[PDB]
């Protein structure tokens, strides 16, 4: 189940708005998750299920679902939020991750 | 809740190794344990999973039938037997958990991998 | 060398008080059950857009309880007239079929819920959502068919009559004249072995196993509580047991193990009606126990 | 079944296969639900069993008992 | 058993009369009483019946809403009061007793013993 | 529940066989009876249910059923058996009587 993530690179400046999109092949009924990975560190969950928000992470991250086009939105960027993001689907085993989106300081 | 990986180390092609994922702070039989890997500067890719209680085990297509996974609920641990390694399997392996909450049975959300580990490096010459 | 002994039962005394009070309670049950079940179905259908994973058994159980409640007014009308049946022939058969199917559906789905809840923390814990969804759908269809098969017979043989002496209509069941006793005992024993005994036994065993498992796991203990788990079994027992003791006592009367007396008929009549009242209270206590308590459900209720 | 869809009275099913020899105690009930009925007590099993009024000897006995 | 009728006599058209059937020699509080007619030179016809112990009553179509029927268990007698008599009621009335045994599908209804009956005229 | 009896009139002689038929416009579960009355006396009961011969009647008369068609059979008509026979049904709360059959030498 190929999961295509776009765009694969960003240059948002501090305090701007960030949007990332993940597109599935088949239909997955709101069983997507969004992970964040720092350079050379263990990934940590950001959003579990299609839209819920993991208890503990800031409220800037917002997850939305539309058909089979999942979207992650960050309202503001802080110096501590410049890393890579992955989208995962937990519906059809095997579990397939995304290609990986990178955000860099402009 | 705390997960720690152990094992790794360079192994010649065609060899085998054991990777141990130990868990603490919770009984292991109420949460599936997954194993994922990351090649140098590449995206993640799922490998294996297991539920300790009844020994259900799935696998990944690219490595179907080449690994073994066995979970000991007595010691709250998971074992991944690696064998028939290729030179292209070098990566870093993490063992994660998929929490299942019982207090919400009828109305629950599709869970995600909550707690990860530092992981261990596996190399092949 | 035999004797003849004549025993005349006095004409049935006033029964306005009992009938009026039971109808009063039935109206309360109807209102308070219909409203609750409708809300649960609405929330379950609406939640799917928020990313939740609602459970099919809850939706099917809610529909079954709603159908059972809808037909209470028919019994209320048929009860104020002291068991007379003014309605037509089709009404009697159709109403009984609806009631029986949608009352066995609820009883079977309770047992299915218990087994699924235990397996969802022991076995299904590492199964893809698609497979468990398919398994639940298959079980849902299977349970519906089984309930329909069990309920069809009694509806087939149902027919109306008009007493030659008293000259008022009635809706009863007529069986083959060569196996009258066998059919009566069989169709009043299937409602006691496939209605209470087996479903309650499975529910008790599997919820006990779930309680043991959750206690053994420290992390689950903090959030969930063991009061609700035992509450499920106790509520089912308290609601249904009195009715299935009255029915089991009615069967004994048929076989004449209990000597007949003028008091037995009145006592059994009152006991059966009064106990059936509680048997239907189970149909409204169900949403208050399975859905109104879950913290996630309440948060979804207010937001919708 | 719901109670309304039921018929309640002393005897709900007859038992024609009975013999005049094995009868010790009769009983002529009279209930508004099922008019006159007959309930007997077999002297072997001591089990109260209904009886069908069509049996000839039953008819003679019952007419004699009631008319007197 | 012995049934005797009384009350038969001349009546003006549109008037009223009251007939009493007295039965001696059986349990009145068990059986049910039946009144039937016989027009002059014609076949029998059913009028009504009363089930004494419980008071259940039924009426023939041709006399619905006109004839009233009562039973006195204390006097073990059956009273039939007729009012608004028409010109087609002149007949001979018979009183019969039937024991309503129970059969699975129907209740016994064979009028066993018939009284001598009395002639009621509407002139 | 209109009930019919045929033939309305009939003739025979001593030592003969006679059959009288009674039909019901609706279904009656073997619930019938047959009386006989003399020209000016009170009627008497002959058969009830469908074929159970009454207590005090001889064996000449015999009743039988077929679908909904109740037949009375009389063999060896004695001189005293010249009367009017009536057919009744009592399934429904509204009883009924037949038109009436007459037999003469
Ligand atoms: C329906 C829900 C809300 C409440 C259920 C309460 C229980 C206790 C109710 C259900 C039916 C009720 C019974 C209905 C009728 C009578 C007859 C009356 O002469 C005495 C009380 C008695 C015997 C009631 C006692 C209370 C009762 C058993
Ligand atoms: C008064 C009562 C009995 C009427 C209830 C009718 C039932 C059969 C109706 C009510 C709403 C319906 C649901 C409406 C929406 C959906 C979502 C769809 O993706 C699957 C079917 C499903 C889940 C329907 C199944 C049938 C349903 C549950
Ligand atoms: C005797 C007759 C009237 C009873 C008819 C029962 C009806 C209400 C039953 C028959 C089949 C049932 C459906 C079977 C399967 C599903 C799929 C599930 O995911 C949602 C509920 C839903 C859609 C059920 C709703 C209730 C249903 C439509
Ligand atoms: C009288 C009624 C309530 C009894 C119904 C029996 C229940 C316990 C039976 C009916 C069908 C069964 C299911 C049939 C298929 C499967 C798939 C399997 O991979 C796991 C077990 C599971 C999920 C079964 C569990 C037990 C089950 C739900
Ligand atoms: C157990 C579930 C799946 C099916 C239940 C079907 C019910 C309707 C079956 C189960 C046992 C059956 C009875 C078994 C034996 C007899 C005796 C026979 O002389 C007449 C039919 C009769 C009286 C049957 C009636 C139908 C019956 C009650
Ligand atoms: C007795 C019945 C038939 C009448 C209806 C009353 C029902 C709704 C009552 C009976 C016992 C009650 C339960 C008793 C204890 C608890 C534990 C508490 O931490 C949450 C509420 C909960 C789970 C209650 C919910 C409501 C409940 C189930
Ligand atoms: C014990 C708990 C679960 C309540 C269960 C209800 C029990 C107690 C109820 C159900 C029906 C009731 C019986 C109904 C009829 C009679 C016959 C009468 O002549 C004496 C009382 C007696 C024997 C009742 C006693 C109480 C009874 C057995
Ligand atoms: C602790 C729980 C199970 C108690 C629930 C109360 C039940 C058992 C109560 C509610 C109303 C009660 C009934 C009220 C009236 C009568 C009529 C009487 O002639 C026999 C007892 C009988 C039939 C009672 C039996 C017990 C009863 C059914």
Image (cartoon, coloured by chain):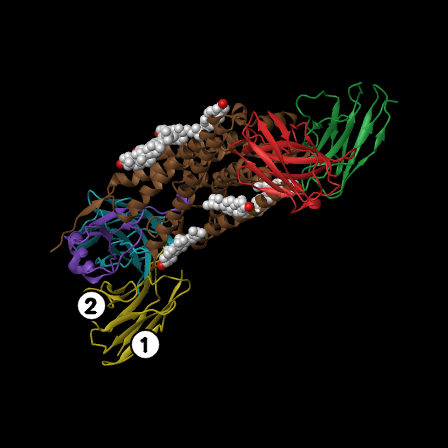
Chain colours: A green, B red, C brown, D purple, E cyan, F yellow
Q: Is residue C51 above or below residue E3?
A: above
User: Residue C39 placed where, x, y %?
Assistant: 59, 32
CB of mark 2 near ligand 5 (< 8 Å): no
Dot 1: few (<14), some (14–19), or many (≥20) neighbours within 10 Å? some
Lower sequence index among marks 2 and 1: 1
Q: Please, which chain is the residue tagged with disc 1 on?
A: F
Q: Quadrant of residue E2?
A: bottom left
Q: Which residue is mark 2?
A: F57
Is label 2 in contact with label 1 (beta carbons under 8 Å)? no
Q: Residue at x 30, y 58 (%)?
A: E37
Question: What element does badge 2 sit on?
Answer: loop
Q: Is residue C137 left or right of residue A28?
A: left
Q: Foreground: B120 or C103?
A: B120
User: Residue A32 placed where, x, y %?
Assistant: 70, 35
Dot 2: few (<14), some (14–19), or many (≥20) neighbours within 10 Å? few
Quadrant (top left, top right, bottom left, bottom right) of the N terminus of chain C: bottom left
Tell which residue pokes out farthest to the left in this image: C1
Q: Is residue A51 above or below residue E85?
A: above
Q: Which residue is mark 1?
A: F10
Q: Is residue A50 above or below residue D55?
A: above
Q: Is residue D66 left or right of residue A82?
A: left
Q: Is residue D7 above or below residue A37?
A: below
Q: How many marks?
A: 2
Question: What element does badge 1 sit on?
Answer: strand
Cα gap from disc 2 to disc 1, whole angstroms: 22 Å
Q: Foreground: C202 or E73?
A: C202
**Front of the two marks 2 and 1:** 2
Q: Foreground: C107 or A79?
A: A79
User: Residue F53 placed where, x, y %?
Assistant: 24, 66
Q: Please, which chain is the residue tagged with disc 2 on?
A: F
């Amino acid at each position: 189940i190929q999961m295509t993530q776009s765009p694969s690179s960003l240059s948002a400046s501090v305090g701007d708005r960030v949007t990332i999109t993940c597109r599935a092949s088949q239909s997955v009924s709101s069983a997507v998750a969004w992970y964040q990975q720092k350079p050379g560190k263990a990934p940590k969950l950001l959003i579990y299920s299609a839209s819920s928000l993991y208890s503990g992470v800031p409220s800037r991250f917002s997850g939305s679902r539309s058909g089979t086009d999942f979207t992650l939105t960050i309202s503001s960027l802080q110096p501590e939020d410049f890393a890579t993001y992955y989208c995962q689907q937990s519906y059809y085993y095997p579990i397939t991750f995304g290609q990986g989106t990178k955000v860099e300081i402009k | 809740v705390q997960l720690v990986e152990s094992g790794g180390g360079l192994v010649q092609p065609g060899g085998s190794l054991r990777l141990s994922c130990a868990a603490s702070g919770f009984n292991i039989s109420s949460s599936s344990i997954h194993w994922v890997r990351q090649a140098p500067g590449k995206g993640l890719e799922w490998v294996a999973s297991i539920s300790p209680s009844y020994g259900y085990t799935s696998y990944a297509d690219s490595v179907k039938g080449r690994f073994t996974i066995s979970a000991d609920t007595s010691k709250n641990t998971a074992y991944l037997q690696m064998n028939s390694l290729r030179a292209e399997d070098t990566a870093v392996y993490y063992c994660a958990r998929v929490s299942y909450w019982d207090w919400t049975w009828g109305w629950s959300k599709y869970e995600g991998m909550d707690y990860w580990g530092q992981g261990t490096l596996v190399t092949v010459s | 060398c035999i004797v003849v002994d004549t025993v005349m039962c006095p004409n049935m005394p006033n029964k306005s008080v009992l009938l009026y009070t039971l109808s009063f309670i039935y109206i309360f049950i109807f209102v308070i059950g219909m409203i609750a079940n409708s809300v649960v179905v609405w929330v379950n259908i609406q939640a799917k857009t928020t990313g939740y994973d609602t459970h099919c058994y809850i939706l099917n159980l809610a529909i079954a309880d709603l159908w059972v409640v809808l037909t209470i007014p028919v019994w209320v009308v048929s009860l104020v007239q002291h068991n007379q049946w003014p309605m037509g022939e089709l009404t009697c058969k159709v109403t009984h079929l609806i009631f029986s199917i949608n009352l066995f559906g609820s009883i079977f789905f309770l047992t299915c819920m218990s087994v699924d809840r235990y397996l969802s923390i022991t076995y299904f814990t590492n199964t893809p959502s698609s497979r468990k969804k398919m398994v639940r759908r298959v079980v849902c269809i299977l349970v519906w068919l089984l309930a329909f098969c069990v309920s069809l017979p009694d509806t087939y043989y149902l027919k109306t009559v008009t007493s030659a002496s008293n000259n008022e209509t009635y809706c009863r069941s007529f069986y083959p004249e060569h196996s009258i006793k066998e059919w009566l005992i069989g169709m009043e024993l299937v409602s006691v072995v496939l209605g209470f005994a087996v479903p309650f036994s499975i529910i008790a065993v599997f919820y006990f196993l779930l309680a043991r498992a959750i206690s053994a796991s420290s992390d689950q203990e903090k959030h969930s509580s063991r009061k609700i788990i035992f509450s499920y079994v106790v509520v089912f027992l308290v609601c249904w047991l009195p009715y299935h003791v009255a029915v089991l006592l009615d069967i004994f009367s048929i076989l004449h193990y209990i000597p007949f007396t003028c008091r037995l008929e009145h006592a059994l009549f009152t006991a059966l009606h009064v106990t059936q009242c509680l048997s239907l209270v189970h149909c409204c206590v169900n949403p208050v126990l399975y859905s109104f308590i879950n913290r996630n459900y309440r948060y979804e209720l207010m937001k919708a | 079944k719901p109670v309304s869809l039921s018929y309640r009275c002393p005897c709900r099913f007859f038992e024609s296969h009975v013999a005049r020899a094995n009868v010790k105690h009769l009983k002529i009930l009279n209930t508004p639900n099922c008019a006159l009925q007959i309930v007997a007590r077999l002297k072997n099993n001591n089990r109260q069993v209904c009886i069908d009024p069509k049996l000839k000897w039953i008819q003679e006995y019952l007419e004699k008992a009631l008319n007197k």
